[PDB]
Length: 333
Ligand SMILES: CNC(=O)c1cc(Oc2ccc(NC(=O)Nc3ccc(Cl)c(C(F)(F)F)c3)cc2)ccn1
Image (tube, rainbow, N blue to C red; front, side):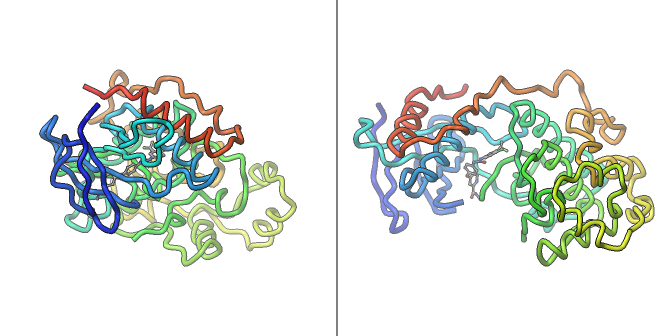
């Protein structure tokens, strides 16, 4: 067992192993830190009140379970997970050790203008990380530029914190009510991000969920009868058919002189019918990614157990299960 040191950072008390040094404030309580074991700079996240309720406790276990499973170059990873607690009995705090994100995707644009090669590389990497995530039966559901970390080498990872409104990137099926989300809600978001990288502008800068859906309809059209077949709710249907028919615009016209192959892929991503949306594994083999695509270096995830999601449990049970997950952590190479 490591040896800890306490400090006030700030009005919060931080208890971390000596391995982590020079903590400075940077989610909900993150310090940048020097990881003296690897020589690297890390994000250390201290969770506030992880076990305060059943919902908080489930949330905490869910995040720990997910971070521990994520083992991909284009996806956030868990460098370490620690508690000062010695026993289940004194177990109250959970700290997450992640690589430090400097700039997100927006910070990267609001620095410099992007080549078509940059869009290719950036969107390649989002899709390759998403391929991995989707294959674990996980759906991100909040993909947007603030959830994507990009280094000085323009290398990218997917994360989720919890600009930059989530709605601008939301699939239309989410802003009505579903549920019965499929994975390609995440492809819509990617579509929305990719257009914005090309255009330098928010594709659907809705003022709210209504104005949002108005903007979406202009570009892609109002649904046709084959999509209207699949809509269950009575209205639901008395909004879409109660709104004047719109033609599906010509993407080539809307997307300027962007690369015509980026215009093709966009078309295939921003389909109003979630069933006809290109998947991540399909998007990787698109001609826009010819310079980056390698069928043999686009890995999938190990099987991922999320049966816990159907369980309603007590705070102490969620908390014990988180404690196990903390104890069974195997630090990566
Ligand atoms: C400017 N510096 C910082 O503020 C800072 C804070 C950091 O802390 C973080 C610590 C943990 C997480 N947890 C996730 O990301 N959770 C996640 C949930 C669902 C899903 Cl689906 C995924 C996914 F997609 F990856 F798989 C990831 C996010 C950020 C890291 C780096 N930098």
